[PDB]
Image (tube, grey):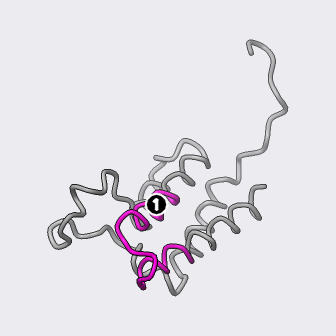
Amino acid sequence: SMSVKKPKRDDSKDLALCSMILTEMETHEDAWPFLLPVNLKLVPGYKKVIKKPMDFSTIREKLSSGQYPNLETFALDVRLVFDNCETFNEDDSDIGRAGHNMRKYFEKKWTDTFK
């Protein structure tokens, strides 16, 4: 509350560390469904169904231009990518499996870097 603060957690390396995680997600062999925005002209149903499209290249541009206020807003966009994937793709599909794989990969790096 006013003039009453918990001890200051050091967030000065968060930008660099999120960038490293994102580089590892970019280079994973199962990243290919997530590298670029879904083409809304060429994929029937995507525009109407997926209210907030997100992909790794859009997160990379947001990260590089100071559009994440803190490390939690960064994780929310990464998780959005996977939530969108599960909304649109069957689990028993190459893309559906890729999304599960990458979500696991992310959540481990997240825990190990920050928790």
Magenta segment's dominant SS is helix
> Residue 15's spot in the image, x, y percent?
61, 54
Point out the residue furthest to the top here: 2
Left or right of residue 81, residue 108 in this image: right
- The mark tally for this picture is 1
Identify the residue at image location x=65%, y=64%. Answer: 107
Identify the residue at image location x=56%, y=68%. Answer: 22
Q: Does residue 93 belong to the magenta stretch?
A: yes
Question: Is 4 or 52 nearer to us in this picture?
Answer: 52
Residue named by callout 1: 83
Question: Is 114 or 53 nearer to us in this picture?
Answer: 53
> Residue 19's spot in the image, x, y percent?
58, 64
Quarter occupied by residue 53: bottom left
Point out the residue furthest to the left here: 41
Q: Which type of secondary structure does the marked residue at label 1 adopt?
A: helix
> Residue 74's spot in the image, x, y percent?
54, 52
Name the residue type under label 1: Asp
Quarter occupied by residue 49: bottom left
Identify the residue at image location x=46%, y=57%. Answer: 80
Q: Does residue 36 belong to the magenta stretch?
A: no
The crowding category of the residue bearing disc 1, from other C-alpha atoms within 10 Å (few below 14, some 14 to 19, many at least 20), is some
Quarter of the image that includes the C terminus: bottom right
Left or right of residue 81, residue 39 in this image: left
> Residue 101's spot in the image, x, y percent?
57, 77
Left or right of residue 48, residue 83 in this image: right
Image: magenta residue range: 78-101
Above-or-below relation of 72 to 90: above
Above-or-below relation of 110 to 26: above
Quarter occupied by residue 32: bottom left
